Image 1 (cartoon, rainbow, N blue to C red):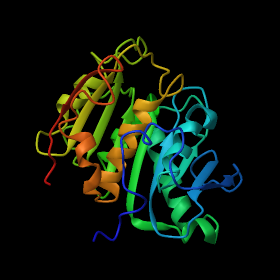
Image 2 (cartoon, rainbow, N blue to C red):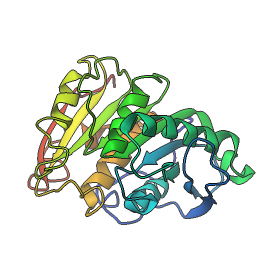
Image 3 (cartoon, one colour):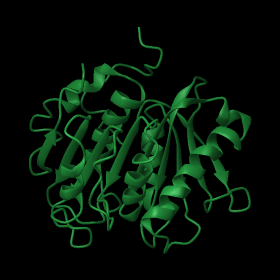
Length: 263
């Protein structure tokens, strides 16, 4: 009955499948066309419909390529997704927040008609790796119209995110020596209010680079999160709640949440 539901009905593995069921196409954004960010690649479903849109930022150094696999596996589940380059690869979290904002406004207002015709302007999300994840917490903390935020192994100097009201899934890595869970991801999770939809999923046997030396767990729970909150798709609730032993214990360290998230 939901206006926003897309795609065949979910089984568990399949979210683990490398590829989702939507065929995907490409739009390349050069630096020349990108006002307030460094360019990027838009991945979008071939099948014509209206879909939520997502912007994804890299971290300190790296690239576009850092996060590509992720943006296009997400698009293959029925989303319009831009993976960006930043103005410089040394840009700090707060600027990456600005650049995420500019990247969303590019897809809705500046891209080809083929891209813009596929986006529902009202249903947006942000994700990012490392400093890019910090940038998404900042953007989330200033745009409570965003439908979801997914910080991946996030890094930020500010640990207090107690003004974020956007549904936020934080993904941490146990072996991360760069943005350690103890002093980044966990403090961020705890600071988020108790009364919003939030979750913390910690990978087991995972470095800082898993969101780029990766695979099936992030893809699965991120798509499930985006489906639930960007698409209002209650069919994905049961992947998230209880989140039982989840995409798997020893692939999964641990999993906190405020389930069930207003069924």
